[PDB]
Image 1 (tube, helix red, strand yellow):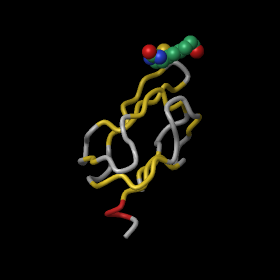
Image 2 (cartoon, rainbow, N blue to C red):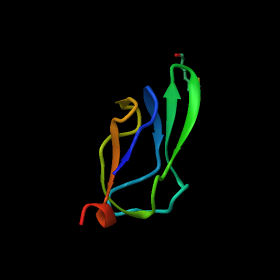
Image 3 (cartoon, helix red, strand yellow):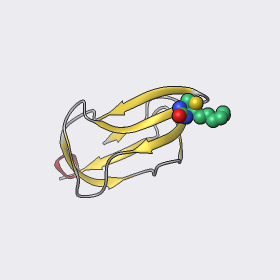
Image 4 (tube, rainbow, N blue to C red):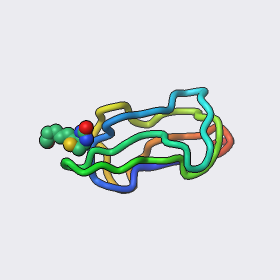
Length: 72
Ligand SMILES: *C(=O)CCCC[C@@H]1SC[C@@H]2NC(=O)N[C@@H]21
């Protein structure tokens, strides 16, 4: 459902399976080779699955989150 938008490392994560998010709420943060980019929910929903973890490597179009309302 939600995906990373820049090359980097998933500095922090703020979602869990079964958690709730709302469009524009902070769900992760990128470090990007010493740059800083908040990662916010592309759409509201209940989280079904987190496709990465805090500290994982990530890239533009790499998966981040899967939502029950979007994986019906
Ligand atoms: C350089 O590679 C050393 C570690 C860089 C960590 C970076 S600096 C910008 C981001 N903010 C932060 O606290 N950590 C990330």
